[PDB]
Length: 246
View (cartoon, rainbow, N blue to C red):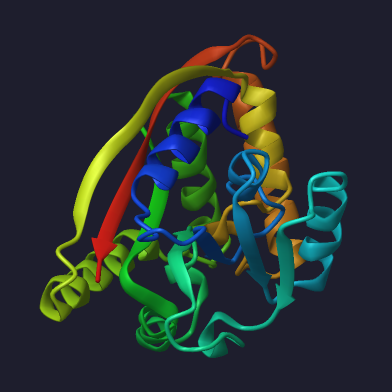
């Protein structure tokens, strides 16, 4: 959940990167999820095609855009096979997807196929600086390893680097820029909850009962080492937008 001003800044940078050459611009988002990224653009009158393979996600998304879905097309499909024509959209938005797909080279390939000449691939991602939340996540990973279930570290990053390689090679000249930087409050309770809810990919591989045991231990460790679990600490974040153009 991005603060209003930040959500606005990201949308603005995204709309600024699309040059529809006299035509009304249309964005396609791969992995729209619940529409955190989509809403700010949809709210501004932009034609939008929201794609997601998760039916439960689209259900929530349809609810959120109620009353502002006149120019929105909801699509349930795998990013691997976009049910759209070659050169049909001006911008393809990809936020936190690469590490979730089995074959990104195919997803990227599909994204490039549906983009019109002069169209732009728009990748975005959050980046947070060290804070007690980082401390808790690392502790979570340590405890998981102690249960005998060590977890993989930073697949998205490596994935983001390989896509970048491909883009340059394809001549899309990927330019990355910081489009927002802010600081929010986060309490130990909130970070622990996010962990409990298995919101992060690195927490979703362990069998349910192992995660339960790790959480029990983590909650106790936080009570012992983090003071008032309802006391806020700062978390500095920035949002990066990498634009590749045809």
